[PDB]
Amino acid sequence: SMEQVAMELRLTELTRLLRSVLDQLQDKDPARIFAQPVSLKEVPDYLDHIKHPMDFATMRKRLEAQGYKNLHEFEEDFDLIIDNCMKYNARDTVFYRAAVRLRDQGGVVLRQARREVDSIG
């Protein structure tokens, strides 16, 4: 139908906007601490601690399959990256500190994304 097509155009455009959001968030991680899944070869107990691992590469795969229906779903995945790290790693570690800085800097990007998503509909 024409409606299914219109709906599909909306999703494609959301995917375009979220791709730009993701790029902007990933720039706030210049050390690439959150770029890839935590390695289960290198951290074999990880899934005993963290039940829903997340990272930027994994978000990107979902995004490119148009697997984010709305901004809420995308933010959920971003918050997992941060929250997983702040639980697994102690406060005095470069990893925890990286997550805090990503959270703080990402807030600004995500604030305007929400306005854009509501605005453009």
Image (cartoon, helix red, strand yellow):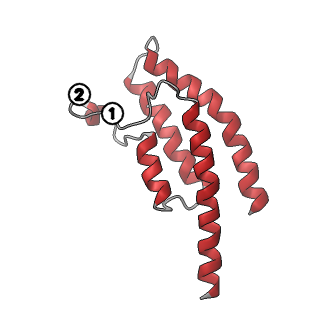
Instruction: Give the quarter of the image for residue 103.
Output: top right
Query: Residue at the location (59% across, 88% down)?
Result: 1
Q: Quadrant of the C terminus?
A: bottom right
Question: Percent position (x, y) of residue 105?
Answer: 64, 29
- Where residue 22 sits: x, y (%)? 57, 44
| Residue 45 point in image, percent of width and height | 23, 30
Q: Mark 2 belongs to which amino acid?
A: Glu
Q: Nearer the viewer, residue 56 or 50?
A: 56
Residue 40: image quadrant is top left
Residue 39 falls left or right of residue 31 = left
**Labelled disc at residue 75:** none
Q: Residue 44 vs residue 53: left or right? A: left
Q: Secondary structure at mark 1?
A: loop
Q: Nearer the viewer, residue 79 or 55?
A: 55
Dot 2 lies on which element?
A: loop
* Residue 47 image position (x, y, % from top left): 27, 37
User: Of 9 and 79, which appears nearest the observer?
Assistant: 9
Q: Amino acid at mark 1?
A: Val
Q: Is residue 116 left or right of residue 23?
A: right
CB under 8 Å between discs 2 and 1: yes
The 10 Å Cα crowd at callout 1, few under 14, some 14 to 19, many 20 or more, is: some
Identify residue for label 2: 42
Q: Badge 2: how crowded within 10 Å, few (<14), some, or many (20+)?
A: few
Q: Pointer 1: what residue?
A: 38
> Which corner quadrant of the image does residue 48 belong to?
top left
Q: Pick the residue in front: 49 or 107.
A: 107
Q: Residue at x 51, y 26 (%)?
A: 99
The alpha-carbon separation of the residues under discs 2 and 1 comes to 8 Å
